Amino acid sequence: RNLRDLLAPWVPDAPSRALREMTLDSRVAAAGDLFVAVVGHQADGRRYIPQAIAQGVAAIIAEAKDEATDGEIREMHGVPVIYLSQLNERLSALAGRFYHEPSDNLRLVGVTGTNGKTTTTQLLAQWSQLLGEISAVMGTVGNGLLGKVIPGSAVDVQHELAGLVDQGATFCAMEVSSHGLVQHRVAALKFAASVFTNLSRDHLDYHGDMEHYEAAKWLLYSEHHCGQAIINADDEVGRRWLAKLPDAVAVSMEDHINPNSHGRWLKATEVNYHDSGATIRFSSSWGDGEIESHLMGAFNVSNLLLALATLLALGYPLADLLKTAARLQPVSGRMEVFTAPGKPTVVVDYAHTPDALEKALQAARLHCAGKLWCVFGCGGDRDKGKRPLMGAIAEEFADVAVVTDDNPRTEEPRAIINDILAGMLDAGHAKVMEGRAEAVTSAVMQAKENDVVLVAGKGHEDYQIVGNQRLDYSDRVTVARLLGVIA
Image (cartoon, rainbow, N blue to C red; front, side):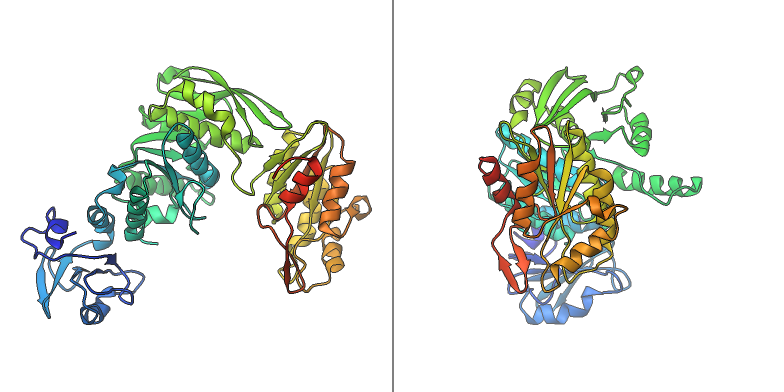
């Protein structure tokens, strides 16, 4: 890593210096580092140029605005300070070159939109790896090889991606936040494909406003190497963009494919939702087929179809994708299904807010021939407002509501339950059982074979906080043991 070669595309005849790490943070800038001094939310990094010189940085690259011309080379105390205009906009490209263009050395797929980003990202990584890639994820949860995820600027993005390259990753599925995109955090990444799970947003009912939003986004995406575009056609904005993009792949599970276009497409023709998942029948320009998904709910059909359409576009053969589909697994703590011969189906989900609980019950309902049971509680010593709302949701969207404890902490457990019951029209119809383990047992043992039992609130968060003590407890372990299966 040499400053001269680093800047060869923008600043010719730049001085020759060995560079260690690249950083925006003057506090961690150490000997031999490249310090990068940028202007942000009224925060000017050029302030700290003396500190960085004092700490022995080999070189500095600094925002040119109001201080220098673009490509201007200065020398402070033997340390080269090179100024560049629009540094924030160029940071990704610069870091890219510094870290030897990691996005040119694996297959990078970007996923954008509000819903289904996290799951679609995971499914891409999982499926690609089943087909022989060594896959990785970059997201909000964290970054890393599949199964070894570790819990942010344009530089960190490139640095992390290089780290994955070094660890042997050949495929990376990356969640791209709306804000990250706008701040140019992924500006120079070479995406092999871009998945748009949805393009719509609230608060745009002025015809003017939707126009500005779309124009801003379209401009933003026009500046990126998006690669193959995979677009959810069950989105209003998605459909409009598809009409302007003849090489984009249209994906639908609500019949929004127009065959007159002769573009590439994939759609679900029918879905049988049953106890263990979904049998998804689909047609596409690559051909037709049937997938046995072990994921629950309609959203996860869409997520899976988006991942499929993407991998098909990237050239993975339909036959191999179909052959590996039954091995796709739920995202940890997210609608994880447990089945056993002659026993009720049990779903463990992290849902701990009114909206998440409603969504989980709606999804579980699709797989439920009999009665839908809901076992849940609310956290103690936290905001109480959600309690009656979660009560009302359980009463409305499930057939049997079993109210129990969920991390009561120092608060009187029964007081929490009362707050939940307060929100119901017919509190007397709820079952209350304290001991969460006992409540789960009560549901599972009483539920019929064609019933579904949703155990909500914890997901994979395997403890029960009672008083000060974090007790060992797991919904997954309890359920598995009751069903005679292995968690």
